[PDB]
Every structure is written in C-alpha cells, then in structure tokens.
Amino acid sequence: MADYLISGGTSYVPDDGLTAQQLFNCGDGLTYNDFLILPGYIDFTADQVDLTSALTKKITLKTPLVSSPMDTVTEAGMAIAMALTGGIGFIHHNCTPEFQANEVRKVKKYYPLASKDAKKQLLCGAAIGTHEDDKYRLDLLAQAGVDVVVLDSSQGNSIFQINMIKYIKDKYPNLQVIGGNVVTAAQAKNLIDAGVDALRVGMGSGSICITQEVLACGRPQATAVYKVSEYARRFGVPVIADGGIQNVGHIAKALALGASTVMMGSLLAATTEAPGEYFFSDGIRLKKYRGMGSLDAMIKVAQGVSGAVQDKGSIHKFVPYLIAGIQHSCQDIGAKSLTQVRAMMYSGELKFEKRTSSAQVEGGVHSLHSYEKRLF
Amino acid sequence: MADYLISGGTSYVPDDGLTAQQLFNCGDGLTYNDFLILPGYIDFTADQVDLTSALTKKITLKTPLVSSPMDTVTEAGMAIAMALTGGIGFIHHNCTPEFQANEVRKVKKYYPLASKDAKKQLLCGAAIGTHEDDKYRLDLLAQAGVDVVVLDSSQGNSIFQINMIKYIKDKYPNLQVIGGNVVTAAQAKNLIDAGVDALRVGMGSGSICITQEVLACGRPQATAVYKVSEYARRFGVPVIADGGIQNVGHIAKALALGASTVMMGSLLAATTEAPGEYFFSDGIRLKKYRGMGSLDAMIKVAQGVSGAVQDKGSIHKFVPYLIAGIQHSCQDIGAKSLTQVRAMMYSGELKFEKRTSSAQVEGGVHSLHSYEKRLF
Amino acid sequence: MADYLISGGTSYVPDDGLTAQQLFNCGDGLTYNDFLILPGYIDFTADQVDLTSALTKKITLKTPLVSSPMDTVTEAGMAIAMALTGGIGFIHHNCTPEFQANEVRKVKKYYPLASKDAKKQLLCGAAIGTHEDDKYRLDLLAQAGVDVVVLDSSQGNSIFQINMIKYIKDKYPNLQVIGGNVVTAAQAKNLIDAGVDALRVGMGSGSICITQEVLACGRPQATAVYKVSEYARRFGVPVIADGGIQNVGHIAKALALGASTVMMGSLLAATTEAPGEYFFSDGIRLKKYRGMGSLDAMIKVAQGVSGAVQDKGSIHKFVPYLIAGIQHSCQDIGAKSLTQVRAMMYSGELKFEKRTSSAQVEGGVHSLHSYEKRLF
Amino acid sequence: MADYLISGGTSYVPDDGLTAQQLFNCGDGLTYNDFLILPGYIDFTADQVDLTSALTKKITLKTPLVSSPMDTVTEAGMAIAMALTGGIGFIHHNCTPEFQANEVRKVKKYYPLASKDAKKQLLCGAAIGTHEDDKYRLDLLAQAGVDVVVLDSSQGNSIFQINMIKYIKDKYPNLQVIGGNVVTAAQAKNLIDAGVDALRVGMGSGSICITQEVLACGRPQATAVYKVSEYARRFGVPVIADGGIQNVGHIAKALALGASTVMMGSLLAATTEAPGEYFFSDGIRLKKYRGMGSLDAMIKVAQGVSGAVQDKGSIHKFVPYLIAGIQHSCQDIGAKSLTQVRAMMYSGELKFEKRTSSAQVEGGVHSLHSYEKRLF
Ligand SMILES: NC(=O)c1ccc[n+]([C@@H]2O[C@H](COP(=O)([O-])OP(=O)(O)OC[C@H]3O[C@@H](n4cnc5c(N)ncnc54)[C@H](O)[C@@H]3O)[C@@H](O)[C@H]2O)c1
Ligand SMILES: NC(=O)c1ccc[n+]([C@@H]2O[C@H](COP(=O)([O-])OP(=O)(O)OC[C@H]3O[C@@H](n4cnc5c(N)ncnc54)[C@H](O)[C@@H]3O)[C@@H](O)[C@H]2O)c1
Ligand SMILES: NC(=O)c1ccc[n+]([C@@H]2O[C@H](COP(=O)([O-])OP(=O)(O)OC[C@H]3O[C@@H](n4cnc5c(N)ncnc54)[C@H](O)[C@@H]3O)[C@@H](O)[C@H]2O)c1
Ligand SMILES: NC(=O)c1ccc[n+]([C@@H]2O[C@H](COP(=O)([O-])OP(=O)(O)OC[C@H]3O[C@@H](n4cnc5c(N)ncnc54)[C@H](O)[C@@H]3O)[C@@H](O)[C@H]2O)c1
Ligand SMILES: O=c1[nH]cnc2c1ncn2[C@@H]1O[C@H](COP(=O)(O)O)[C@@H](O)[C@H]1O
Ligand SMILES: O=c1[nH]cnc2c1ncn2[C@@H]1O[C@H](COP(=O)(O)O)[C@@H](O)[C@H]1O
Ligand SMILES: O=c1[nH]cnc2c1ncn2[C@@H]1O[C@H](COP(=O)(O)O)[C@@H](O)[C@H]1O
Ligand SMILES: O=c1[nH]cnc2c1ncn2[C@@H]1O[C@H](COP(=O)(O)O)[C@@H](O)[C@H]1O
C-alpha cells in the first residue's frame, strides 16, 4: 500500500495554470473576456449538474439567473416568467409607489424549477430608492409582502443607505435587503457591518453605463466580483454580479469567480416579457432598452444612455439555453455543483489563465468569409 | 590550442532573446501571432531540410500536415490527396458507421512523399466518438483496417474516454489512438497514463470554435501546445496542434513550440477535395465550412458556427507551398530538421521574443494605399 | 442553507504563510534550521497519531526512523533493536562479505511496533557496493535472504549503479533496491527509469561529510528532500533523507517536506547497540563515530572525517522519545497521519515560513546565564 | 523511431537548479563557500579525467595549479617543484633584479606531467613591476629567457600598465604578459584591448589582503572570476583566480566558474620548497607568510599583513592530492575535461545553487564532540 502512503488518494496533478489570487493580485484590471478558465477532470454527465445557488442568507434559488430592475427590462411579467424557471426578478422603482405595489401584488397572486415560498407563492423581489420619501414606498411593499429588496444606488457606500438599512432591520426583521453597488472591499465592509444580507457588485461595467467615462469611478467587473466575493464570504454573504454580460460565457465565468447569482440586464432585455412593445428600424425587430442614469428617467447629470437591442423571443426558450450553458461549463470545468466550483476556485484546485488581445480576437470566429451564428 | 581549451568548440553567442520557458512562465496567455522566433545561423541550402515528423509512437510521416475530421473538410478524397503528399487524414464520424466504413475502405484500396504502410497501402486514419454505441463503429473500422483513430471530444479528460482507451488497448493492441482535446498538463497526464499513443492539443482556439466565448473553457493555443508538448515528451508522446492556423507562419511556429504534427482545419477547407461543391455569393467562389459544435450536426447547446471560406484550388498545388514555407522557416531558424528545431528549442539555443500589438500591426502590410497579396 | 452554498464546508482560512513551492522556488538553498512549519487546527489527541510510513514500494514500516549503514553506528545489534521498534537497519559493507552474511543471518534468526515479515521474521536491510566484485556479496546476501538493499554511493547517477540495478532486477525480482545518493531531479529521473524502488536523498549535508567543502558537490538538504520527493511521487517512489539531523525537529520537518522515511546517522550513533565500546576523554563517556569517506576506511582522496560523539544510552529509551516528538509535531501541525501531513503539504493547506539568522539565534535558548537542556 | 523524432537524443532532464547567469545577476556578491555545484551524470572512471588547462593564448599546462609571486611562498625551488608536476610558478619581484635573474636562470638550467617547452627546458614565469625602472628588470629577464611575465599590481587598470604592455608587445613579440588585478569587466576590456594575453582576476579576497577593509575597493571573488571570465572568452583570453582559496573545493568551483587556471598563494605556503625555514610557536611547526602590501616589503599605507601558517610538507605529496580532488569534483559534476566543465557551465547544462549560512555551517562538520580532519 506504499503508493497510497506517499501522498494519500490525490495523484500528482501538475502545476499548469494560475489560481485566482495570483491572477487578481498582479494589479491589472482584468474583465470577463480577458481571462478564461482551464478545464479539469470530469466523471459525470451533463444533465446531473446541480446549479442550486443562494441569493441572500435565507433565500436560495434553483438557478443563479436574476434580472436587473430597470424600467425597460422587467415588470411583473418577466418576474413571473423567471419565477417559473427558478430565478428571481426585481421591479424597478421608476414609477409611482402604487404602481410598484400593484405590480408586486400581481406577481404573488399568481415546470419543476420552483422558486416559490413556504406557502407556495412565488418568490419575487423589488427595488427601492434611498431618499427619505421611499419609506412610504417600502412600507406599502411590505403590506404587499415583498421578500427581498434592492437598495438600488450608483454608490453603495452612502450614509443614507446604511441609515436605511438600520431603518428596515429594526422594523422588518424577516425582510431582507440587497446592498450595492460596491466594487471594492472597503464599501463591502461598510455595508456588511450594517447588516446587509447580500451585496450586488459592479458599477460602471454595464451595457448602458458610461459613468466610468463620465464620472471616472468604478472598476473592471471581474476583479470587482472576485474581490468583493472574496471579502464577503468571510461573513457568509452572497454577491450579485451586474453588467458586462453579453453571453452565457460571461455569467459562467462570473459566478465561477465567487459570485453566487448574476444579474442580467441587457441579455434579458428585448424579450416577450419586456415592457413596451417591439418596433422596427432597418427591418430589424428590436425593443428600446434604457437605464436610469439616462436623462429620460423623468441642471442634472446623465450616467446612462437610451438605446435599443434586437429581440430573442420568450425567456422560456431562452433561459433553458442559459442553464444548459452554465451546465456544460460546470461540466468541463469539473465540478458537480456551483458550490463545488467555488470550492475548487478558493481551494486553488481550479486554475485560470490571463489572455492577451490576439488570443481574444482568435477566441471568437476568424479566418473565414461569412458565417451564421445561432446559439440554439 | 588555448582558444579551444577555454570553452570548447562553441563561440560566445551573446544572450539576446528569450528561451521558451522564460516566455511561457510569465503567466500571459500568448498565442501564435503574439510572439515570433528569432533567427540563428544557417550553413545549408533550403532544399535539403528534412521535415520528417512523427504522428504517434509507431507512425512517422514525411510531412507534419494533418487535417481535422469535420464533415465539411475531409473525406476519402482529401485523405488520398494528403496520403499522396506525406500527410494523414481523418474521416469525420458525423455519418452512419457503414458510410465511414466504405469511406475508409475507399482510401486504402487506392510523388515521392510516401506515407504508405509496410504493404504499400496508404496510411489513413479516422475519428470515432466516445459514447457506448461507438464500439459498433470502430470494430467495423478495424475490419476495414484503420491504423490510427482519434477519440474526438470537446473535453479530453472524461471517464468515458479513458474507459474507451482501456477498451481498445486490450482488444486491439496494434491499433493506436489519439486522445484529446487537452490544453493543460493535468489532463495530458490523465490521458497518457491510460495508454494514449499521441495527443491532439487545443480547444476553443479554432476558426469555428466559440466555446471560449460560450463555455468559458479552453486556453490560448500557443501556451497549450508548448506546455502539453513539454509534459508529453517526458513519456515520449507526440502532440497535434489544432486551431488558430491562418497561414504557413502559424504552423511553423506551432511545431517549433514542441508539436510534432499540426492539424489544419480551415486552411485545408474549401479545396477541390473538400465535400459538397462550390457556390457563389457576391461573385466569390466559396465553399461552406462548418464545425460539429454548430447545431447543424444533425434543448441542445451550440459550440460552433456554420459558415464559408473562399477557395484555394487543389492541395497538390497548395501543400507544396506549405512544405516550402516550413522548409524556409526551418532554414532561417537554423536547423536541418524539425527534430533539430525542437532540440534547439528545449536546449535553450533557439530563442523567442514576445511581440506587442503595435509590432503586430506593423508585422503585416502597412503604410500603403492598396496591395495584392498572392502567396504563390 | 445559504451559508453552505457560497463555498461548501470550508471556512475562510486566511492566507497567512507560504506554501512549499513558493518557498523552494525563490532560489535560496534553505536547510532544516532555516525554515519552520506554521501550525494549523487540531481536533484530536496526541496518542492517536499514526506514523505509518513506507520505505519502498512494497515495504511499509510502523515508524519512519531508519539508520545509515556506517561501520561506526549499526550492526545486527541496532538492527534487531530498531526492528523491535518499527524501524529498519542497514548493515555497512565495510567488512568481508562473509561477515556481512553472518551479520544479516544473526538479525533474521532472531513491543507492538512490529516491522517483521509475512513469516514473522524481522525486516532487516543491508548495504552493498557498486563495483563488479560486489555481485559475490549480494548473491550470498540473497542466500541469507535480505529483503531491501542500499546501493550506497557518493554519486547516485553512475553508469555502474544503473547497470547494477539492471543486474538485480532481472535476477532477483522480489528483491528491492535503494538508489542514491541523489540531490536533484535529473539523477532522480535517471535512477527511477532504471527501476529503483526507493531513493535515498542527500549528499554532503552529513555530520561527517566535508565533500561539499572538498569536492564542491551536493546541495542543501531541505531543498533536496523537497525536490527529489516532489519528482519521485510522480512515479510513486518514496525517498529517504540523510544528514543534517541533530534533533527530533529536523526529522519531523524533513519528512514533512515529502520524505517518507528519514535516515539517522549521527543521532543514532553512540548508543549501547553501536559498535566498539565506550571510552573517555575529559571525563565524558563517548564513542567514536566515523564515515566511509574518511581515509580510515581501510593516492586516495578523503570525503569524511573520523571523530566521536557523547552517548545517549539505549535506543529503547531513545526512539520512543523520537516517535513522541514526531507525534507532537504532527499533532500541532494538524494532521492525524504522516500521509495527511504530506497531503496537506502538496495540497497547499500546510504552510511554511522562511526564517532569518536572528530569528534562528532567538529560536533556541537565549538571554540567560546558564541552563540544563534535558530532552527526556 | 518516433521516440527519437520528438526531441532527438537528449532525454527530458528536469529543470532543477540555477544556471550561472541567473545566479550571478541577482546582484548579491557571492563568494566560493556561499554557493555550490549540483551534480550531473557520470559514465566514466575517476582516473581518465583530463585536467589540461590553458595559461595564456599559447601556453597550456597539464594542471591548472599556479602559484602567486610573493616573497614568502615561491622561489626557483617551488618553481622547479611545480614545473615537475605540470603547473607554473612566478618569481616575486621583491628583490634585486640580478637576484631575480639568477633565480630564473636556476629554474631553466634544471614524473609524466611535463610543463616544459619545445626544447625541453622547464616553463617558468616571473613577476615584474610597473614603474619605469622595471624595464631594466625585464630586459635582463628576457636575456635569461623568461616565457610569461605577470604585471603585478593592486589595480590592473592604470595608464602605467597599459603603457608597459605597449612597451613589451612591440619589443618582445614572443614574450607574453599577465595583466591584473581586475575584478570587473570594464578594466578587463581596458587590458584586453591593449593586447593582454591572459588576465589574473581578483583583488582584496586574498588570505593576506585587507585592502577591502582598508581601501574599500575590490569585490567578492566568485562573482569576479565569473564575470571577468565571461567577458574574457569573447576575445579568447584565459583568466587566473587569486585569493579566497582554503581547500581543494574552492579551486574546483573556481575554475568551474570560467577560470582556466587558479593561483594558489596561502595553500601553497609553508611547504618544504617555501622560503626561509620553519620555526616553532606553541609547539606548532609553522613558517611565516607575508604579502607585499604589508609594510615589511622594505608616509606609506599598508594593504596587507605579516603572519604565519602551519606546514603541509612537500608539494610532491600535496599537489597529487589537489589534482585528485579536482579529478573527483570533475567526475561527479559529470565532465571528462575542464573544457567540458566550462562548456557545460556556459551552455546552461551544468547548474548551481545559492547556499545560506545555516547550510554553510552544516556543510562542514557539526553535531559531534571532537574530530580529526586529515585530508590525505
Ligand atoms: N453600473 C451601475 O450599477 C450603476 C451606475 C450608476 C448609476 N446606476 C443607476 O443609476 C440610478 C440612479 O443612481 P443615483 O444613486 O446616482 O440617483 P439617486 O437619485 O438615487 O441619488 C442621487 C444622489 O443623491 C444622493 N442621495 C441619496 N440619498 C439621498 C438623500 N436622502 N438625500 C440627499 N441625497 C441623497 C446620492 O449620493 C446620489 O449621488 C440608480 O437607480 C442606478 O440604478 C447604476
Ligand atoms: N476546439 C475543439 O477542439 C473543440 C471544442 C469543442 C467542440 N469540438 C467539437 O465538438 C464535437 C462534439 O463535442 P462533444 O464532446 O461536446 O459532443 P459529444 O456528443 O461527444 O459529448 C457530449 C457530452 O456527453 C458526455 N459524454 C461523452 N460520452 C458520454 C457517454 N457514454 N455517456 C454520457 N455522456 C457522455 C461528454 O462529456 C459531453 O459533454 C466534437 O466532435 C468536437 O470535434 C471541438
Ligand atoms: N553524504 C553522503 O551521502 C556521502 C557523500 C560522499 C560519500 N559518502 C560515502 O562515501 C562511501 C564511498 O563513496 P564512493 O562512491 O566515492 O566510493 P566507491 O569506492 O564506491 O567509488 C569510487 C569511485 O569509483 C567509481 N566507481 C563505482 N563503481 C565503479 C566501478 N565498477 N568501476 C570503476 N569505478 C567505479 C565511482 O564513480 C567513484 O567515484 C560511500 O559508501 C558513501 O557512503 C556518502
Ligand atoms: N588581492 C591582490 O591581488 C592585491 C591587492 C592589493 C595589493 N596587492 C599587492 O600589493 C603589491 C603592491 O601593490 P601596488 O601596485 O599598490 O604598489 P606599487 O608600488 O606597484 O604602486 C603604487 C602606486 O603607484 C602607482 N604607480 C604604478 N606605476 C607608477 C609609476 N611609473 N609612476 C607613478 N606611479 C605609479 C600605482 O597606481 C600605485 O597606486 C603588489 O605587488 C600586489 O601584489 C595585491
Ligand atoms: O442608467 C444607468 N447608468 C449606469 N448603469 C446602469 C444604468 N441602468 C442600469 N445600470 C447597470 O447596468 C446593469 C445591467 O447590466 P447589463 O445591461 O447586462 O450591462 C444593472 O444591473 C445596473 O448595475
Ligand atoms: O464545431 C466545433 N466547435 C468548436 N471547435 C471545433 C469545431 N469543429 C472543429 N473544431 C476544432 O477546430 C479545429 C480546426 O482548426 P481550424 O479550422 O484550422 O481553426 C479542429 O481540429 C477542432 O479542434
Ligand atoms: O564518509 C562519509 N563522507 C561523506 N558523507 C557520509 C560519510 N559517511 C556517511 N555519510 C553520510 O552521512 C549520513 C549520516 O547522517 P548524519 O550522520 O546523521 O549526518 C549518511 O546517511 C551518509 O549519507
Ligand atoms: O600584500 C598583499 N596585500 C593584498 N593582497 C595580496 C598581497 N599579497 C598577495 N596578495 C594577493 O593574495 C593572493 C594569494 O592568495 P591566497 O594567499 O591563497 O589568499 C595573491 O595572488 C595576491 O592577489
């Protein structure tokens, strides 16, 4: 038995690759399509990967796909749509409080991926501001009975947001909050000590956000979702990644970096459950998609744009492709669960590699005349 | 004789350049058109370079040019075409097993670059899957008498592939296998210990592959073909480089990094020996070229695209240009053989240099109005 | 259950310390009393640590304490003494072959730590030279029935030693050999490929050896026993650490670096089971202790000295102190077995720290007038 | 033959160790007993190593052991003694020119290691000053017919020494000179361009020299004999290492660093062929040994001391031990010649390792009461 008593169970497993901390302490601000994940060993099929992920300290979901509360992406409609497929939705606060109240009533007065509560009503969350008049919003939201709320802000480290956190945690102890936006560990600490139940991480790296180009704030997305998640697991706090998502690759490598759920704003935009309706320009069927920092929210500054993106049909045909993509990525990484993927990442077993710009432009399609890219 | 007794034969030879391990342990994921090879000393003509390279542990070839088994590039046709010019071909498994059987019979029932066996029948290989029903494929392929097989897979480190390797190495001892795809040394170890006779290295970096952009797996190609070849020569195992080939430069610097043969998928596509036939779009005579990970192979995910590329005529006028390109590159590097090129690389004598993006965009044509680029 | 689905089982465990490869790739040639091992977490008592370690690929022992074959330390006497307490002994070859034959017969013709074979005769090994006349030694040793032999040499990488290994592995397949001395991975490879069953690592760092000061060869001991053991576990080969042992600390941190057994030459010298008998100088009861490289082995060069060391009584009172020391060190490191200690070392969980000369001179006793140091 | 066509002849040979330039470009001023040489592979016996080394561009010797011209070590006596055993000697210039003239006549008017010229008279060299009156010395030395001269100086980079080199190279073209002392590459260039035929490298690191402690000049010895030899082989110039020699280890690792011959000042002192005669202090038979920078050479400064060292008998019993030591070190390094040792060093095949102070104090004898160290 001498071949066992040298090391014990584990084979040699040569040291090719870079672990997470030697990748994110080189100082360079890497983003999603700037590194990539090296594979490992698989001993299991694609179908049996369990993507059960946690949203906050008491709310777990069957899929990590959550949506961002903008007025051009989610309502009660894609809320009930993602609640039917395991995710969660948040209702934007850019409306009257009574409209958000009857919106959050419409979803809870309403396929094995459950995401519904103890009394089999659907989990659904919402977004609330941080000004003093927003108390009159979320008290009516509690009468409607919302379960998790998002303290949506450009800067997550205000005196106003931590005062609001102290205002709900004494009044509403069962209710849970989502602090953000944070990008660094200092404001992550300054929210977690206030009693935040989960963070939403990432500012500036949105498909709409130009606040890096306008306010010079923020940081690259992947370094943020690594370091805030690395700090947040010290206290047992999940994080939520926003922005910089264009495909099923970015969300997979995003929650492989320590995130538990990922927040999809543009890639869930222009669906059949999205607000408004379709229109046409140059014969392309597309729906407008607009952030709050654009001046079309209602001496002001603008931190966002107004634009549009082509459609992708219903989510009920779209998010099974997303979970199949997460499912295949967590296959060929080599873990049977997302929890095992983060365990292999923080354990140093799962290894990465930095990627240069030429390997980026060869990572996609190249050296051909024309092509049709259909993902499913 | 004192000028000999200081060092002995060798002159000073100043230390300009970087050797391979100081280039590929900086952590950056370099690819083919991101570094380049510094020249040395030549004392010989272009014609007498011997590009004899090994495919697997008993199969050697007169040229290192092998093709990739897709249904849009090779059949028996370019198999007999590359067997006539020293290479090898593999028949794609995206057909019925009887069609692959009569395909591999058509090539062996059939100009000094030989690549034919002891009984002067042509060397020709094929590709086989990894599912349980594929036993009924490769047993008929053995009745047809194929010599080397490729266990084609997206992820080379499965329990299924090593179980298949154990299934052919006890049944068919003379038959030889090609494991893959691997990109790192760990799965290279986990295939070589099973009894793999040669690897095929490189995933995601294909001209069709978007699985880096979709599944977040893989790594850059040049670092993969350096490190898997650096591990594989410990056990005397050749490797085969796939993807990221656009020209005769990439294959030359690819097999200069430790690869013995290189696998050409797109640059051998759209030939007279390619499947289907030509068609026209915008007046350009081009042939469709499609990978298996595209959904046009037959709830599914897609790891490839369907597209097309312009033609290059017959290979019998094309691969002499490729071997002349390899021949001139191995000239001005300074080695009389590919084996001497790898000996100078692992010995530290042959040296490289990293290249930046501005030196990349000046490496090609620049500072002129228009040009005609004809390679031969 | 959200506190489990972030990481899974494992707590935060901050990154204080250095793992083994970042300690032994800084280039500095660290030795035993130049680094030290940081503690971890214990959840078990001192008595239940299992120090079962492997000698070669089929020979496992209950303690890792083996002795070095010099003519001034071991005979049949300390062979039966260490066989009674789980270890192994080797009989020096600096005698006539008939004397080594009746020595190895005396030990096998002869307290729960067993170290005896299938037919309950004591495991005992011996040492054999490498010259051509030594065939007539080890064939008589096989008639006496020795189980493991040590191809004792100053340089383990000779053509003569690998020819000898090929000479016993075809004649005597059940018999097992110990190659050495090696200090680097190249000669470790050049012995393992010949069929060596276990290495003995470390030259020059002995208490007698001045061959570093005379032949300028060798390397520091701890870097050798890390790197040769790191190479040797690729093929499932144990290593044996010689020299530089003054205390129970050095052997503990020595086999914590990848060694399975450790070879004790001077710290087992001057016992009641040691050759010759005691004598007196300045009223101190001490026994002479001499290596083979001294000119007193029988135009010659000398690689050793002749000297003496004070006594320590019987080993049966001494090696229980040694196993209690190993037992307490493997306690406060935090592993229930030596195999778990090497698993935590190669896994990166067990961490080290380099130590400077001032922390060395404060690591021992300091800042007092006089002291009595009694270890048990 | 595929196992040959991957690399060609050379096996894997793992990358354990440090080559010379990564050891001597870390910036630390390493000396002889601060690093050590890792072994390699041997396929040959000890007796057949050929230590033929070159002194200057036309003078080769059978052993690299030369002596330093002080008035307390060499005369005609140890000149004829080392000429009988292959070396060379130099006669100190601290005498009248007629005394040096009849000294150099006594040696040439006078066992297979030859070191004698074309007309079978003994090779013997001498040392000459650099002041203007020294012309009247070396012209009489040329009438006596000396073959190589040493332009002995504390600082080898004077205008006076290069003017002297221009003064002998036009007058005496067959005569050859030894420039020095140099420690850096700049003064090595400024002597080689003048027409120096070989350098003598190393100031301050002598057993007598306190000019580092007094004039703050010089550098550590091993870095000097690496870098001046690395510059000097660009022009095909041998170098001669002085000082810091206490044993046969230092001269072996000294000429392994690029030196061709090594200059022995103290370890050849106090012999039967040394000047003066023996005397006694505390019952130890010892002979006085004094450098020129001491004030006992004849407002002055002193760069040396006057002292004594115990005897070692005749050199004819002593330098066979030295060549046997060089012979065994060049054995277990793994080269059949000194030229092959320098070829393996500059080729990067021969590798080193830095050594710390604790591994230094364990490199010698330790952990014992008392010992007798006899080297032969
Ligand atoms: N990438 C991102 O995540 C990102 C980045 C920028 C903006 N945004 C979007 O822009 C929206 C608006 O951002 P915003 O926070 O700047 O608008 P806001 O109206 O919520 O706050 C405006 C400013 O007033 C301050 N503030 C907050 N509460 C206050 C109070 N009681 N009294 C006085 N001042 C108070 C804040 O510091 C803020 O700078 C957000 O809903 C967010 O969704 C998102
Ligand atoms: N750049 C590249 O080299 C690259 C990358 C990606 C895909 N591809 C191409 O895509 C093709 C298909 O790739 P694929 O391997 O994902 O498709 P596949 O049908 O061969 O395997 C599908 C999945 O099932 C699993 N599998 C394999 N054998 C199984 C078995 N008996 N039972 C259950 N599951 C099994 C595998 O893990 C795999 O994830 C390949 O032929 C390959 O050529 C190439
Ligand atoms: N720290 C250490 O481990 C260490 C270091 C040095 C020496 N030693 C001790 O010194 C002892 C003697 O060492 P040694 O190997 O130098 O003495 P040796 O008599 O075994 O070998 C002497 C030399 O002859 C060569 N040799 C071996 N077999 C030969 C053969 N058939 N024919 C011709 N030459 C042959 C070897 O290369 C060696 O240099 C060893 O038993 C060893 O225990 C130990
Ligand atoms: N480790 C060493 O190698 C080392 C170091 C220091 C000294 N030494 C010994 O000390 C001895 C004396 O050393 P030294 O060179 O300082 O004594 P020196 O008498 O030869 O020279 C004395 C000084 O005068 C200068 N000099 C040389 N030629 C001159 C000339 N024509 N006119 C005017 N000035 C001139 C020199 O620069 C020197 O500083 C040397 O023989 C040498 O062997 C050896
Ligand atoms: O108006 C805006 N200005 C700046 N950032 C915004 C704005 N609206 C939404 N965002 C961010 O963009 C994210 C959506 O991600 P994306 O659309 O997929 O890039 C949200 O979660 C917000 O963090
Ligand atoms: O469908 C696919 N999805 C991803 N990679 C593919 C697919 N088909 C072929 N490949 C890879 O692409 C390589 C062809 O190289 P290229 O076409 O010259 O870039 C093959 O050897 C495969 O490794
Ligand atoms: O004579 C010798 N010269 C050099 N090394 C020796 C000699 N004799 C024994 N050794 C080494 O010293 C080790 C003993 O370790 P130590 O006595 O505890 O320092 C042995 O295992 C040998 O490797
Ligand atoms: O008087 C002196 N002052 C400083 N260095 C000296 C003196 N005399 C000799 N040396 C140097 O010491 C070397 C002798 O080496 P060692 O005696 O073996 O240390 C000579 O080759 C000179 O370079």
Image: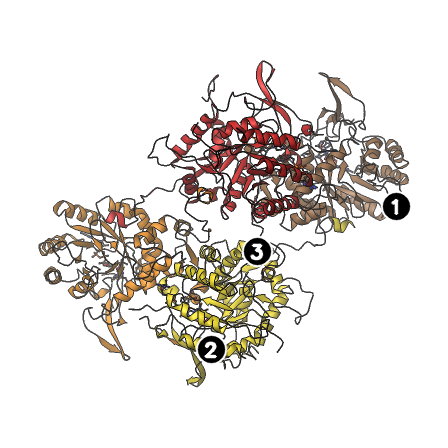
Chain colours: A orange, B yellow, C red, D brown
* Most foreground residue, C128 or A44: C128
Q: Position of residue B312 (x, y in %)?
A: 51, 80
Residue on which disc 1 sits: D118
* Residue behind mark 2: B103
Q: Residues within 10 Å of mark 2 (few under 14, many from 20)?
A: some
Of marks 3 and 2, the one in the foreground: 2
Seen from the viewer's position, the closer of residues C298 and C44 is C298
User: Where on the picture, by quarter, is residue D77?
Assistant: top right
Disc 3 residue crowd, few under 14, some 14–19, many 20+, Cα 10 Å: many
What's the distance in space between the residues labelled 3 and 1, CA to CA? Answer: 46 Å
Q: Is residue A259 left or right of residue D336?
A: left
Q: Quadrant of the N terminus of chain D?
A: bottom right
Picture disc at residue B19:
3
Residues indicated by labels 1 and 2 sit on the same polypeptide chain: no
Q: Residue at x 37, y 59 (%)?
A: A332
Whether A290 is drawn above or below B105: the answer is above
Q: Say if disc 2 is inside 8 Å of ligand 2.
A: no
- Image-quarter location of ligand 6: bottom left
Q: For this rendering, which residue is in front, D111 or C315?
A: C315
Callout 1 amino acid:
Ala
Q: Earlier in the sequence, mark 3 or mark 2?
A: 3
**Residue reaching furthest to the top:** C283
Q: Secondary structure at mark 1?
A: loop
SS label for mark 3 = loop
Figure check: C169 above or below D83: below
> Please, what secondary structure does the residue beneath circle 2 have?
helix
